[PDB]
Amino acid sequence: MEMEKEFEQIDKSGSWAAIYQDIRHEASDFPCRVAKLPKNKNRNRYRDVSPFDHSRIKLHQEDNDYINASLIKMEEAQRSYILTQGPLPNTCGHFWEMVWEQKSRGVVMLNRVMEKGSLKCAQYWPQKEEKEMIFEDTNLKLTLISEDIKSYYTVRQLELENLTTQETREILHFHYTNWPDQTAPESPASFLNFLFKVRESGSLSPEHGPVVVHCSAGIGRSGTFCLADTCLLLMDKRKDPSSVDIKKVLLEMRKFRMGLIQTADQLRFSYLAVIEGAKFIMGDQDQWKEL
């Protein structure tokens, strides 16, 4: 693969930090005026991570429509993702409102609630079947239906009810619990197995709304998730799978959300995940589950 042999050329040349920062200099810049309004300051987890006005998810509440979330619309791949920050104590009803209004079927969570001794994310879903959550501001009810806790991830079925209309949807919650606290994983095998469990679930199907993906800021690990999924898709449909330039895909995603892929190490890991993932989607997954 030209991806694989450019990978080695970067590894032998030790120039990941340079490749990465070229990406940072070429990345798009668009205005974020709504994110920056004083009335929205307490709706943002980091003052330096904001959604572009042009691609932001608008809540359909009449008062304040703001939420720190971005629609990543990948035209050629024919896949959309919503990348958002980890909910704040005060934005958990906003988060489920978005899930409801965008008709999402899956929520992908790439961080632990606590990491490096701090809260990266509010406890926004119920932990016991018998103690559901009611979000009074957005009039939503969230019930844990089942958990399947595995080694490196946990899948949850949740029931989201619109208390106004009383419809209910099943939401699948995919929680990658194994990402180290200060580095990308040593092997992409665990991560690729997680991506493919999300794929198999149907939460990425075009019949549903965009999957909601978040980590703490919603740009780093979230960026890795969508970037590797989209490259594997394009490899699957392009007739010339060798032609997928992961850096040109990243810059296209960065038209929709700033800062996707936070470190040169994450960039290196995304290469690995795509390279390793291409080996399944071109002829040969059973050995990822093993390790």
Image (cartoon, rainbow, N blue to C red):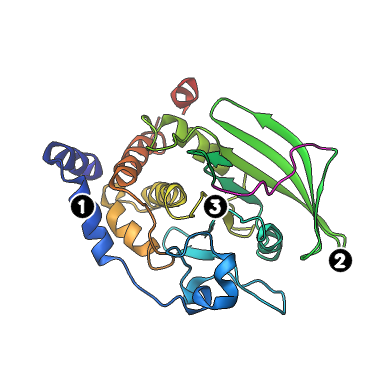
Left or right, 22 with respect to 137, comes to left
Q: Position of residue 183 (x, y in %)?
A: 37, 37
Which stretch is magenta?
A: 120-129
Q: Nearer the viewer, residue 103 or 181?
A: 181
Q: Which mark is residue 164?
A: 2
As drawn, which residue projects farthest toward the front? 117
Say if the magenta span includes residue 36.
Answer: no
Q: Position of residue 132 (x, y in %)?
A: 82, 45
Q: Which mark is residue 288?
A: none
Callout 2 amino acid: Thr
In the image, what residue occupies the spot 27% across and 52% down?
243
In the image, what residue occupies the spot 44% across and 23% down?
287
Q: On the image, numbered disc 3 is attached to which residue?
A: 213
Q: Is residue 200 visible?
A: no
* Mark before the other along the chain sequence, 1 or 2: 1
Q: Position of residue 204 (x, y in %)?
A: 57, 51
Say if the magenta span includes residue 126.
Answer: yes
In the image, what residue occupies the spot 40% across and 64% down?
258
The answer to which image quadrant residue 185 occupies is top left
Q: On the image, numbered disc 1 is attached to which residue?
A: 19
